[PDB]
Image (cartoon, grey):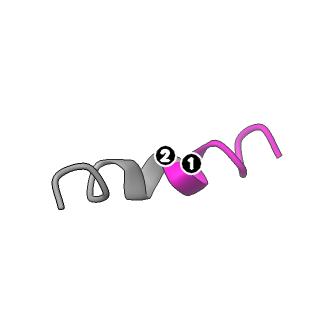
Amino acid sequence: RMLLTPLAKIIAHIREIAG
């Protein structure tokens, strides 16, 4: 779960900043 925890953010932190 150490691969989905830190990625859980970027998973949506790149769709709002870039669209």
Question: In this image, 2 relative to 9: left or right?
Answer: left
Residue at 43% x, 54% y is 9
Residue 1: assigned label: none
Amino acid type shown at disc 2: Ile
Instruction: Say above or below: 12 vs 17.
Output: below
- Residue type of the residue flagged with mark 1: His
Establish if 4 lies above or below 13.
Answer: below
Q: Quadrant of residue 17?
A: top right
**In what element is the residue under mark 1?**
helix
Extreme residue toward the top, this view: 18
Q: Residue at 26% x, 58% y: name it.
A: 5
Q: Position of residue 18 (x, y in %)?
A: 77, 37
Disc 2/disc 1 C-alpha distance (Å): 4 Å
Q: How many marks?
A: 2
Magenta range is 11-19
Q: Nearer the viewer, residue 19 or 2?
A: 2
Instruction: State left or right for residue 9 relative to residue 14.
Output: left
Callout 2: SS: helix
Q: Which residue carries the number 1 mark?
A: 13
Where in the figure is residue 15, as x and y percent of width and height?
Answer: 71, 49
- Residue at the image position 29 percent from the left and 49 percent from the top: 6
Q: Please determine whether, in this image, residue 3 is positioned above or below residue 1.
A: above
- Label 2 packing within 10 angstroms: few (<14), some (14-19), many (20+): few
Q: Main secondary structure of the magenta part?
A: loop
The N terminus: image quadrant? bottom left
Q: Do the CB atoms of the residues marked 2 and 1 lie less than 8 Å apart?
A: yes
Q: Which residue is mark 2?
A: 10
How would you rate the neighbour count of disc 1 (Cα within 10 Å): few for under 14, some for 14-19, many for 20 or more? few
**In magenta stretch: residue 16:** yes
